[PDB]
RNA sequence: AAAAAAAAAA
């Protein structure tokens, strides 16, 4: 998705809500942003508009060139091959200059990984673990939909270059900006994925309870019974609560859950029942002044 | 039982009335150590940045012409007086004073009719910061070598600072010492509301569960008893600090539960505690929903239908609504026979 | 969509407006004060009249040209054929007997010219539509219909009695009472537009050549104007701040 | 329903409907002849009726 | 702070807010078996008797009008003049 | 309807009853037919005093006052407001003198 | 282009100063109020670069009608940012000419130390200040600004006796108001505002300078 | 609004529009380029070669001392024509915005394209200055790029920075026309030109050469407050409210609007209808706590011992007393001597 | 009997 900001420090933003297919460790939002021109600095006037990247689990702002060097591309021609597909285009070569000028100090992969790891939450010590932590950001958090295995840095660099290419296309006006209320960019969670998410949560709770029971009965040197290990009330009670109440999550943590997902079926006319069975709800709350 | 009644059949131990007659009477809890009142916290630092941290005197002396001009300008407006005094005391970082600090002249005879000068202790006032209810002090310029540059300030230290402020400095500070002394903003004796404020919720026969304020006061009593047991046994300093932290948390979340930066008071049923501020503040609160907008007794409400045969100063009323609604007509000799046949 | 989004901030604006002005009340001295007694207006709406009993009036002396003003408002006694067609012989006998008459009609014309200049100063864009109590055209029509006024027959109303009745009516139509300089000045500042409308409509030309009002019709009109100007005054104790909100 | 005669007199002398005809908001009546009453007023006061 | 009768500066005309409470208080008084100052022609609702003896200005009520400087003027019923 | 409840005389009703200038209808709908109450208040301290109505005794604990006790009619919601503020370490002293 | 524009703005500022002095009740002749641009160019010159006129040449000394020994100086300093040195020079001129009232037409602004000098020097000599951009427009000639009349203590006392008012119950006007700075109102005075009304013709209100 | 010949002629009104509208270097030029020019008299651009030797034939500075880097700015002719600008004004603006640091050379008037050449002179007296460390040491082409962005995105050629688009038009109704009184005494409306500007700066518009200082106003209430005064704020708020209500054709009586306009302007400044203008008044505590921020207002009144004098309507509503308002603004006394013959 | 949520009417 590509959006434009009327107010703020960003001229344009590029957003992806990337998630691994039918898996846990939920959806991570990756941003590739352009810095706005309206920065009152003498030295930044020669710089101009600049491209940064906002990473999951990192509260700081990282330039994209350090990220590209952290994926194993020390040269600049290879990265500009990854972003600018046609070398004959003048204006995109003019737009890629300030990121290259800013990230001139970092020129090696481990230096880029140390740059990444120094800005994460709860930073490590003595560089290399941070570098290891940087790999944990660059393999499990950056774009899980393209791959979380090893040796997937090439495809991830291709997709990151495609995102920067789209951001530069939308900066120069060669493509239209994306629309939030365009319904092609929307999906409908029916009973299937929603009950699948509930079963993920309840199965994780069941595995945790079974693990605690067998860890209690394994430290005494004795064996255990599998039928006594599984507490069968967990899945049944969780599904019954989240279908009867409508609060879509844990019973103790229902404040963070969506309400009104499950509703009492309206039996007044046949048309009322058919309209209730074919209802689509928008997740926007009913207090928005925006039309 | 000394605070009031409990059910519809009992009597008050104090005033010997029923639930309608008894207004309910207050109790008190003597805290072992003083704790901050949370809603006065934004007031309290406003006095803490105007008086000295050591000698408890004002940063600018009250015989200043600017203070006299502020007092002359703000007669009857103590809040604006506090605002102007806080603006005057915002730039003061040293407790400057001393009657012998103006000896710049040579061969000057001392004056027996001289007014007293500023009685400053010559200490640097720390910057006071806060991340919730914890209050810290930092000295950018160092005092004498026995003072650490960064300290945590307990409520007992603030209580001892605000106790030694004279009544004149309170009066220039916009707080009348007859009713509103500053050292009374730190909770040492907690009032206990009567049973009318916290009703015992009865469900089926007997009162099973109380409301949230009774459970919160139970937490208050348990934390206070734990603190006085731990200081009576002479335990370690971290145990005492943890007890003060829990007692301050319980007092503040009895008073205020919606302040950011502070952990929420976790009620049993997955909800936050509804404190006194949540009772008062709001559209459905005690002011807007119960005082400006209380429900009436003699009223009716139904669907309307047109009637062109009625004149504009008439309304058609159904017979059931007319039988339910009554009017208390006085009995006069003019209508005595008609009211007799009515009864 | 437009009906839903708005309704919340409209109600919030109404609540804010009604809470800012909930205790603003016309007091018993005619002044308008809030709960703390702080003075807001010396008279309610700058004229001390309630909003229910006022109407849209046409001020006739603003938009006219100079020659039209002199043609339609300057009373010329020298046209004796018009004086025989308009007035009876008793009125012509009465006006010729008194010596005050010519200078009194000239004083009327001077007051009309000064009122025209003040009205043109107050309204610079030439608005001949004011909001004033006591609709004079409808009351003149009412006293024409009640007393069966014949507009093609000579009348018995001398213009000096018209001047005396208008002056007595404007002296009895007060808003700010008292005899001090401040009280008198506030009285004419409150009743300036009403006095200009009275003099511009109850002129000695319109009530004699156009309306042809009789004597008792004229005192009935004067008494009704005075009574209904009294009735249009704002009641002390009326909550005008909440009404305004 | 008012429950006292002073409140009853206040309803009579202030709150009653014919006293509330004229808005103080815009010095105009708030109540007018509406719907088929107005339509038949227009249809009755024609010349040919 | 009793203002003298010659020094009263308030209006001499009873407005609707005085009229409503005078009629209500007088109706409550007649309903609580006070003597009726005027004759009767068969009226039973005491608010009608209250208007009937308000027409002849025979109601014993002193209205204490409060000026904004916390001074008060006392006006009798017959000193005021009815308008409607 | 199911709990046999009265109608909500809300804020806007109070607004336009202020606009009508009817003080007695406001006092009726907001004090007389909603929640009247009588409290006994110490004259010196202005707080709620002990009142035993059987033997007709009055006593203020905070002032040791037995005689100078007045009686104030007020809405019950105002009494809960004052007692909740007394739990807020606030003294809303109703100076009845 | 600098000389003609500077002469024009100096003529406009001088005209506004003389209209301000006439509105305060000071003795100002009719030809000073009706002074044209060509009359200013003949009287003072037209080349402000070569000191024709100089900024110190345009000093205006004016006197009051009722009391001829109550006078105003109007100074036109050439420095854009005014320090304590020029303020002290003007103050020494005020002692050696025995005049308690002066207005300094600054160009850019003043240092806050000079503002504190004006504050604590005030209850012997009144030393007001004005920006040059504020004096290019006569504020009272705008159609949104009604007639303001300063009242004496006798008229204020008569007002408070007639309307039974205390001084805190009146409406207020700030001392930093452009109209109050135009009329030189100190704290405690009462200004009478006469405005045109669309329901009563005209309306007189009163405000207290605070 | 305009006066004199600007009011009736479109050319002088367009001159006023050019003097008011913000025209930077963005709105006027065609393109920018940075060249390396080793020989200024033998420059790489042949089209410049016809006139650059004209400028260096009698130069004001040594051509050896200048830096070889060149900034070539080609200007659009139609934007120069629309803004009525000329190249000597641009050169003068450059020379007063950058001083003697830059050399500016402009093209001829009747050329095909309008070319500007900007160079930097190497100040050799400033090259030996000490105290230079960790200051992001400067190359000349980067300095030319940064000053190019500086004079491109920030340099004002004419107008006011706070004013955006400016429209020039003739009104068609009798509201924005000038209404005068003729010799016959009638009212004549004259259709003079006027301007509508987005963005307001009244000190920099009223003080212009040919702008009416009387009829010119704004829709910004705060700017009316720092420009004119509080009574002009009252009149301006009444005018904006009238325009807002007259856009939809709704009519409200003048008294209900003038009352609000006098309520806001009563205290001498702008008293907004928010929690920042109502709760900052001198009213009672129960009146202020009934609107917004109930607990904060109540505890501020507790800490300051504020006395509520029971004069508002909501205060007596809370007390349940008859409120001193409406028909409760007086007291009824029983006349003892009027109790004549009854029954 | 309380609290929360959902569906609605004007
Ligand atoms: Zn009891
Ligand atoms: Zn000290
Ligand atoms: Zn007591």
Image: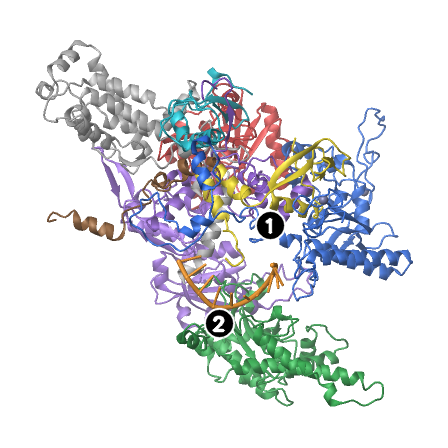
| Residue corresponding to mark 1 | B286
Q: Mark 2 falls on what kind of element?
A: loop
Q: Is residue A192 above or below residue D4?
A: below
Specify whether residue H330 is in view: yes
User: Chain A appears in which tint?
Assistant: green
User: Chain E appears in which tint?
Assistant: cyan
Same chain check for tags 1 and 2: no
Q: Name the side, left or right, on which A59 lies relative to E42.
A: right
Location of residue B15 (image quadrant)? top right
| Chain represented in purple | H
User: Chain G appears in which tint?
Assistant: red
Chain label for disc 1:
B
Q: Nearer the viewer, residue A20 or H117?
A: A20
Specify whether residue C114 is in view: no
Q: Residue at x 68, y 44 (%)?
A: B23
Measured from the top left, where is residue C226 in percent x and y?
31, 25
10 Å crowding of disc 2: few (<14), some (14-19), many (20+):
few
| Chain represented in orange | I
- What mark, if any, has residue A282 been given in the picture? 2
Measured from the top left, where is residue A211 in percent x and y?
74, 84
Q: Is residue B240 above or below residue B341?
A: below
10 Å crowding of disc 1: few (<14), some (14-19), many (20+):
many
User: Chain B appears in which tint?
Assistant: blue
Q: Name the side, left or right, on which A44 lies relative to C52.
A: right
Q: Residue at x 12, y 49 (%)?
A: D49
Measured from the top left, where is residue G50 in percent x and y?
48, 40
Q: How is the image coloured?
A: by chain
């Amino acid at each position: 998705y590509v959006f434009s900001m009327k107010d703020g420090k960003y001229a344009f933003k590029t957003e992806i809500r990337s998630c691994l297919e039918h898996s846990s460790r939920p959806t991570s939002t990756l941003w590739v942003n352009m810095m706005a021109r309206g920065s009152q600095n003498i030295k930044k006037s020669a710089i101009g508009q600049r491209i940064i990247a906002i990473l999951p689990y990192i509260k700081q702002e990282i330039p994209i060139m350090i990220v590209f060097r952290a994926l194993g591309f020390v040269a600049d021609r290879d990265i500009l091959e990854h972003i600018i597909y046609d070398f004959d285009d003048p204006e995109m070569m003019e737009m890629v200059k300030p990121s290259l000028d800013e990230a001139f100090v970092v020129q090696e992969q481990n230096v880029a990984l140390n740059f990444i790891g120094a800005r994460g939450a709860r930073p490590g010590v003595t560089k290399d673990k941070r570098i290891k932590y940087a790999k944990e950001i660059l393999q499990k958090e950056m774009l899980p939909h393209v791959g979380v295995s090893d040796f997937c840095e090439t495809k991830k660099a291709y997709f990151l270059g495609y995102m920067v290419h789209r951001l530069l296309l939308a900066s120069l006006g060669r493509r239209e900006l994306d629309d939030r209320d365009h319904y092609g960019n929307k999906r409908l969670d029916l009973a299937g994925p929603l009950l699948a998410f509930l079963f993920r949560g309840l199965f994780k709770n069941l595995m945790k309870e079974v693990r605690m029971y067998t860890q209690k009965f394994i430290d005494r040197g004795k064996d255990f019974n599998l039928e006594l290990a599984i507490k069968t009330n967990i899945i049944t009670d969780g599904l019954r609560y989240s279908l009867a109440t409508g609060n879509w999550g844990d019973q103790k943590k229902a404040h963070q859950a969506r309400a009104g997902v499950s509703q009492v079926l309206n039996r007044l006319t046949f048309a009322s029942t058919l309209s209730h069975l074919r209802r689509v709800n928008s997740p926007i709350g009913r207090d928005g002044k925006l039309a | 039982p000394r605070q009031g009644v409990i059910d519809r059949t009992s009597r008050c131990q104090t005033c010997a009335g029923n639930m309608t007659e008894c207004p309910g009477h207050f109790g008190h809890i003597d805290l072992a150590k003083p704790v901050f009142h949370i809603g006065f916290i934004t007031k309290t630092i406003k006095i803490l940045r105007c008086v000295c941290f050591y000698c408890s005197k004002m940063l600018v002396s009250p015989h200043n012409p600017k203070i006299k001009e502020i007092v002359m300008k703000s007669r009857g407006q103590p809040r604006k007086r506090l605002a102007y005094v806080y603006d005057l005391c915002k730039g003061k970082t040293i407790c400057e004073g001393g009657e012998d600090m103006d000896l710049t002249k040579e061969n000057q005879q001392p004056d027996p009719n001289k007014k007293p000068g500023h009685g400053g202790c010559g200490h640097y006032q720390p910057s006071i910061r806060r991340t919730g209810l914890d209050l810290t002090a930092e000295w950018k310029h160092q005092n004498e070598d026995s003072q650490e540059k960064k300290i945590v300030v307990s409520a007992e230290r603030v209580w001892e600072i605000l106790k030694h402020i004279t009544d004149e400095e309170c009066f220039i500070l916009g707080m009348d010492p007859k009713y509103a002394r500053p050292d009374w903003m730190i909770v040492t004796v907690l009032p206990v509301p009567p049973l009318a404020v916290r009703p015992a919720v009865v469900m089926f026969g007997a009162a099973k569960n109380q409301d949230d304020l009774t459970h919160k006061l139970s937490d208050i009593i348990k934390a206070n008893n734990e603190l006085r047991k731990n200081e009576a046994s002479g335990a370690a300093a971290h145990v005492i600090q943890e007890n003060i932290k829990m007692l301050q948390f319980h007092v503040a979340t009895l008073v205020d539960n919606d302040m950011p930066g502070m952990p929420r008071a976790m009620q049993k049923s997955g909800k936050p505690l509804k404190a006194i501020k949540a009772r008062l503040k709001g559209k459905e609160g005690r002011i807007r929903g119960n005082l400006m907008g209380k429900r009436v007794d003699f009223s009716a409400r139904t669907v309307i239908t047109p009637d062109p045969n009625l004149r504009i100063d008439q309304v058609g009323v159904p017979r059931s609504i007319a039988q339910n609604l009554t009017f208390p007509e006085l009995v006069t000799p003019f209508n005595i026979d008609r009211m007799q046949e009515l009864v | 969509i437009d009906t839903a989004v708005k309704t919340a901030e409209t109600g919030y604006i109404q609540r804010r407006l009604i809470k800012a002005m909930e205790s603003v009340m016309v007091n018993y001295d005619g002044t308008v004060r809030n709960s703390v007694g702080q003075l807001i207006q010396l008279r309610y709406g700058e004229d001390g009249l309630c909003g229910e009993l006022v109407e849209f009036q046409n001020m006739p002396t603003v938009k006219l040209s100079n020659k039209s003003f002199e043609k339609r408002f300057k009373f010329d006694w020298s046209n004796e054929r018009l004086m025989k067609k308009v007035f009876t012989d008793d009125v012509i006998k009465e006006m010729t007997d008194s010596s005050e008459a010519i200078q009194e009609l000239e004083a009327e014309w001077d007051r009309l010219v000064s009122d025209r200049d003040s009205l043109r100063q107050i309204f610079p864009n030439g608005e001949s539509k004011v909001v004033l109590p006591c609709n004079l055209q409808r009351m003149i029509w009412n006293v024409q219909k009640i007393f069966h006024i014949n507009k093609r027959l000579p009348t018995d109303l001398s213009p000096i009695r018209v001047i005396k009745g208008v002056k007595t009516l404007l002296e009895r139509c007060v808003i700010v009472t008292g005899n001090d300089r401040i009280s008198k000045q506030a009285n004419e500042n409150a009743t300036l537009l009403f006095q200009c409308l009275i003099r511009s409509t109850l002129c000695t030309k319109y009530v004699s050549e156009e309306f042809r009002l009789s004597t008792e019709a004229f005192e009935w009109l004067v008494g009704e104007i005075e009574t209904r100007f009294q009735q249009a005054q704002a009641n002390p104790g009326e909550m005008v701040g909440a009404l305004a909100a | 329903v008012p429950q006292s005669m002073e409140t009853r007199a206040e309803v009579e002398n202030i709150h009653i409907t014919p006293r509330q005809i004229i808005t103080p908001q815009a010095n105009k009546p708030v109540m007018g002849i509406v719907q088929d009453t107005l339509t038949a007023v227009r249809k009755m006061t024609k010349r040919d009726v | 702070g009793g203002v003298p009768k010659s020094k009263r500066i308030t209006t001499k005309y009873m407005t609707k807010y005085e009229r409503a409470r005078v009629l209500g208080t007088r109706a409550l008084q007649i309903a609580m078996c006070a003597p009726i100052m005027v004759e009767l022609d068969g009226e039973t609702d005491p608010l009608q008797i209250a208007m009937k003896e308000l027409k002849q200005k025979k109601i014993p009520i002193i209205i204490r009008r409060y000026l904004p400087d916390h001074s008060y003027e006392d006006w009798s019923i017959d000193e005021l003049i009815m308008v409607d | 309807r199911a709990r046999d409840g009265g109608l909500r005389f809300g804020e806007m009703e109070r607004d336009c009853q202020i606009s009508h200038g009817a003080a007695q209808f406001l006092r009726e709908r907001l004090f007389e037919v909603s929640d009247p109450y009588r409290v006994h208040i110490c004259n010196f301290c202005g707080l709620i005093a002990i009142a035993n109505l059987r033997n007709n005794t009055f006593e203020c604990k905070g002032c040791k006052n037995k005689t100078q006790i007045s009686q104030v009619r007020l809405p019950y919601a105002a009494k809960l407001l004052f007692q909740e503020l007394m739990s807020m370490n606030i003294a809303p002293r109703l100076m009845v003198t | 282009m600098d000389d003609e524009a500077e002469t024009y703005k100096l003529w406009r500022i001088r005209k506004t100063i003389m209209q301000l002095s006439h509105d305060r009740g000071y003795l100002v002749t009719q030809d000073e109020l009706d002074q044209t641009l060509e009359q200013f160019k003949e009287m003072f010159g037209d080349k402000p670069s070569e000191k024709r006129p100089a900024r110190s040449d345009l000093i205006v000394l004016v006197a009051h009608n009722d009391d001829p020994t109550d006078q105003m100086f109007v100074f036109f300093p050439e420095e854009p940012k005014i320090g304590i040195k020029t303020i002290k020079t003007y103050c020494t001129r005020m002692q050696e000419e025995n005049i308690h009232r002066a207005i300094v037409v600054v160009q850019g602004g003043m240092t806050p130390s000079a503002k504190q000098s004006l504050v604590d020097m005030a209850p012997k000599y009144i030393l007001e200040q004005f920006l040059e951009s504020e004096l290019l427009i006569n504020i009272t000639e705008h159609e949104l600004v009604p007639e303001h009349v300063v009242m004496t203590v006798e008229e204020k006392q008569e007002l408070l006796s007639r309307y039974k008012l205390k001084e805190n119950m009146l409406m207020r006007i700030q001392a930093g108001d452009p109209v109050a700075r135009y009329f030189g109102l100190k704290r405690g005075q009462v200004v009478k505002i006469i405005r045109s009304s669309e329901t009563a013709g005209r309306y007189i209100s009163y405000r207290l300078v605070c | 609004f305009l006066t004199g010949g600007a009011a009736r002629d479109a050319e002088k009104a367009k001159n006023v529009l050019c003097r008011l509208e913000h025209t930077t270097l963005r709105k006027v030029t065609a393109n920018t380029a940075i060249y390396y020019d080793p020989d200024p008299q033998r420059t790489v651009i042949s089209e410049d070669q016809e006139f650059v030797n004209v400028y260096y034939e009698m130069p004001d500075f040594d051509p050896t001392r200048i830096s070889p880097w060149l900034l070539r700015i080609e200007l659009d002719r139609k934007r120069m024509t629309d803004k009525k600008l000329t190249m000597e004004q641009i050169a003068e603006k450059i020379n007063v915005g950058f001083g003697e640091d830059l050399n500016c050379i402009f093209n001829d008037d009747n050329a095909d394209k309008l070319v500007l050449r900007i160079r930097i002179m190497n100040n050799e007296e400033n090259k030996f200055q000490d105290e230079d460390e960790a200051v992001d040491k400067m190359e000349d082409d980067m300095f030319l790029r940064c000053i190019e962005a500086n004079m491109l995105s920030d340099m004002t050629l004419q107008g006011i920075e706070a004013i955006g688009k400016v429209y020039m038009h003739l009104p068609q109704t009798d509201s924005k026309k000038r209404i005068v009184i003729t010799e016959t005494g009638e009212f004549k409306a004259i259709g003079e030109w006027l301007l509508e500007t987005d963005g307001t700066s009244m000190m920099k518009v009223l003080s212009e050469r040919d702008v009416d200082p009387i009829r010119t106003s704004s829709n910004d209430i705060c700017e009316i407050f720092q420009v004119l005064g509080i009574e002009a704020v009252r009149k301006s708020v009444e005018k904006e409210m009238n325009a807002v209500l007259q856009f939809y054709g709704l009519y409200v009586n003048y008294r209900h609007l003038a009352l609000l306009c006098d309520v806001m302007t009563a205290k001498g400044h702008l008293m907004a209808i928010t929690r920042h203008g109502i709760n900052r008044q001198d009213t009672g505590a129960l009146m202020r706590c009934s609107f917004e921020e109930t607990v904060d207002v109540l505890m501020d009144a507790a800490a300051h011992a504020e006395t509520d004098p029971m004069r508002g309507v909501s205060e007596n509503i809370i007390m349940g007393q008859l409120p001193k308002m409406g028909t409760g603004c007086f007291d009824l006394l029983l006349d003892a001597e009027k109790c004549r013959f009854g029954i």
